[PDB]
Image: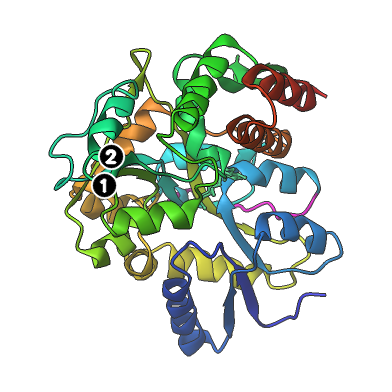
Amino acid sequence: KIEEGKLVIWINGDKGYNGLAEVGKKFEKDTGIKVTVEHPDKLEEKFPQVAATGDGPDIIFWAHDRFGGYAQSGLLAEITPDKAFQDKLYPFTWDAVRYNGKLIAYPIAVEALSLIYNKDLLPNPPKTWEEIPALDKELKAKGKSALMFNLQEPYFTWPLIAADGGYAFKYENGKYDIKDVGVDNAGAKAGLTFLVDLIKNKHMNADTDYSIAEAAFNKGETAMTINGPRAWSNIDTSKVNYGVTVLPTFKGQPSKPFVGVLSAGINAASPNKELAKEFLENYLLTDEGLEAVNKDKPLGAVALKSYEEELAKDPRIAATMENAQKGEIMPNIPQMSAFWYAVRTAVINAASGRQTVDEALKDAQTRITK
Ligand SMILES: OC[C@H]1O[C@H](O[C@H]2[C@H](O)[C@@H](O)[C@@H](O)O[C@@H]2CO)[C@H](O)[C@@H](O)[C@@H]1O
């Protein structure tokens, strides 16, 4: 069981967890309530396992796409902030955490992937994905490469797959059709074929992950990378002269990144629900609270209107929002977990050459509509 009179918080290890730990220390000085911040590996998978038994953290942080599945299993408490508190966050961020008409989380920040480039290697970023093979050929002649990014997580390849027609679930009439899936369609095959051809032609390696791409870019070995807000702090330290901009178009269509709203849910088994609420509304969801996390690892565009006005001046945040406006808020429906696992498998098999693109996407389509 969860201990009473204390707060345990789980947040991903790529977030500003030290910063969040500081907001917890502030809460503890004022109220006497100890706050413990942890970042278990695979917490988005572990949470449903432990929460099912009345264990786990009092508060869990993740993008909103996972939350409909948790709420469906009865693992999240319904939150009911008063209208006054609600008016402080952007309306659309509240929409991302509404499930079956109920609020199941507090929206924290908005994030989308962007194109990041080394201005010393590339004064101007490519406008199309199609010109990258040629950029790479010339950069290779100088000992560098054009682009390196995480190919192990479908989140990073999805903008290209969706660019010319790929989609997860058909949204229509204020509802998602869990039977109308678009991973096996023409647009999706075109996008993933482009990706697989980059690897075949030696422009990228199928095994590239987050650390391999980060190391290469921050070292000045590659002219471009694709990443989210959290990557910015480490690039700042690298002293690389970088720019953050809009992703390239594919077949003349803009890349469409999935947009995630970092959110905070309260475990339905938690005996400390009123403490969690006090912490979230009066300590974390304040200019001071968000600034502390943001300083540890950039949150992106925050849900709190008052603090977002100040961050909006940052060109990196502008680029982030521009990429978001071209993408799509991820669905929060329970089927999202099956979508993500099926698309991860498809991308890795196709990229590693274990299956062809058609075989890979066909299996995913089948799995998701099961
Ligand atoms: O790649 C599948 C994965 O994508 C998203 O996870 C993101 C997350 O939203 C970001 O905050 C950051 O942590 O990077 C993750 C990708 O490594 C989905 O939110 C997640 O459910 C999904 O499995």
Q: Is residue 180 visible?
A: yes
Amino acid at the residue labelled 1: Gly
Q: Which residue is drawn at 46% across and 72% down?
A: 20
Q: Can residue 100 be seen in this view?
A: no
Q: Residue at x 31, y 28 (%)?
A: 132
Amino acid at the residue labelled 2: Lys
State the mark number for residue 140: 2
Residue 70 is inside the magenta segment: no
State the mark number for residue 265: none
State the mark number for residue 143: 1
Front residue (pair 65, 27): 65
Residue 31: percent from left, percent from top: 52, 85
Q: Is mark 2 on a helix, strand or loop?
A: helix
Q: How crowded is mark 2: few (under 14 residues within 10 Å), some or many (20 or more)?
A: some
* Contact, mark 1 vs mark 2 (Cβ under 8 Å): yes
| 330 vs 41: above or below | above
Front residue (pair 334, 285): 334
Q: Residue at x 55, y 34 (%)?
A: 330
Q: Residue at x 58, y 85 (%)?
A: 33
Q: Is mark 1 on a helix, strand or loop?
A: loop
Residue furthest toward the top? Answer: 186
Horizontally, residue 331 falls left or right of residue 225, namely right
Residue 82 is inside the magenta segment: yes
| 334 vs 209: above or below | above
Residue 300: percent from left, percent from top: 36, 51
Q: Give the range drawn in magenta.
A: 74-84
**Could you tell me what secondary structure mostly forms the magenta stretch?**
loop
The quadrant of the rendering that contains the N terminus is bottom right
